[PDB]
Amino acid sequence: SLPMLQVALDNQTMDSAYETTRLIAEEVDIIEVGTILCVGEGVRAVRDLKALYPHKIVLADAKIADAGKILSRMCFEANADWVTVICCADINTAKGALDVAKEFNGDVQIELTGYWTWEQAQQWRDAGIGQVVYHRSRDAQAAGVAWGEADITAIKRLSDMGFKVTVTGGLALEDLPLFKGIPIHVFIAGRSIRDAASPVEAARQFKRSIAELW
Amino acid sequence: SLPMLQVALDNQTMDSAYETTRLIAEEVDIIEVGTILCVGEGVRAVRDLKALYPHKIVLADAKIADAGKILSRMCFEANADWVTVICCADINTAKGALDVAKEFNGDVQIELTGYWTWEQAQQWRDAGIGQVVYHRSRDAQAAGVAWGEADITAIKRLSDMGFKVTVTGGLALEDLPLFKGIPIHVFIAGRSIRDAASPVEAARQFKRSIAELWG
Ligand SMILES: O=P(O)(O)OC[C@H](O)[C@@H](O)C(O)NO
Ligand SMILES: O=P(O)(O)OC[C@H](O)[C@@H](O)[C@@H](O)NO
Ligand SMILES: [Mg+2]
Ligand SMILES: [Mg+2]
Image 1 (cartoon, protein in one colour):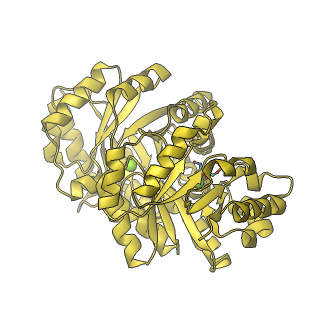
Image 2: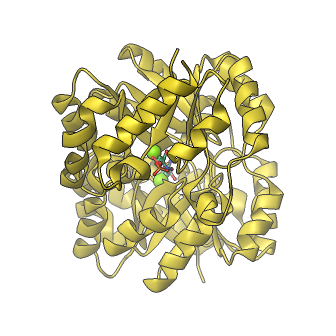
């Protein structure tokens, strides 16, 4: 339907995350336990946030690189809806995580941060993967890498292959028009919501502009 | 120089990890906080293990994919000696982690689990990475991927490029002779030590075989 709004909780502690959820939990559709929070607090972050917000989709942004069955199971036992597996994981890592996701009626997203190939994209599809995260790396961003037409072309191509596409990577309100006409599953905002002078206005403006555009 | 021995603590909780370290802390060179323990407990696992064993090298196997400076700094502020960065991460992720590692007199390894290229390997060298982890994925292993000749050639080639190479991925004692003749920096064992009937004896066996094969 409309692209969903996901907030990324890239916080080092639960209390710092709650400074954000206490403002905007009900202003978004998906609550992400960011990688920073996974590492900071471990999978307790997942269990706690779902207990708080059981009606929201909770994503554990673990960026699983190996041990797909074990790491996926930990996140799902903690009541995750969705987990991420990093694009360079062995194909059997993605398969494994996907098998466990199915036991729990959750799902796996392949996280397209850094280097990957079109052949691997095909492999994910054959394995049954239905979601990808098209992601301008935070560190690439800080080195001056901008969003551009090659990203739009790549997102359209992933969409045509059958994936539901999330878009993320230092997204600002003003960025949303670049993706107009594409059936984007989710837009993620971390900093542009958490660090805004008004996190509630920031999230409502993302939701408004999405409604305008789609 | 003998390859060193690293134990991987791929435990879901600290107490499970301690059931291993109380036995083998003194039998190995590097204590790894496994990716599974980092995700199970968070970076506290790093801080606590270092506090128990401050004389040992502690490796935080975070497999950082992005946000190099932030994630590295969390690990290093928890008193990690080494952190890992996954090989597909944007080159600025590695660079970012390395800069932080240098503030703490630490170091970064690139984790070669999954796909990568030789030009990328050169980029790592130019950025100043000195260590790589040649890793047969646990899940590749489970699907029947064996160690083989192609792995020898790649390892030697990494070493010739100037990297200290760590080898890992379901290693059993019988696999060590595959690598004889190559200046391997570290072998990692997780399951083969932790799940042995006697972890102590398992670690000692690895050390004996290493000392015979590289002596
Ligand atoms: O909008 P951002 O601050 O970039 O956060 C969203 C992004 O997807 C992060 O959670 C992330 O995973 N960075 O790697
Ligand atoms: O010997 P193993 O049980 O395979 O554990 C070592 C390995 O390096 C793990 O710690 C790991 O990182 N797997 O991805
Ligand atoms: Mg994230
Ligand atoms: Mg490990």
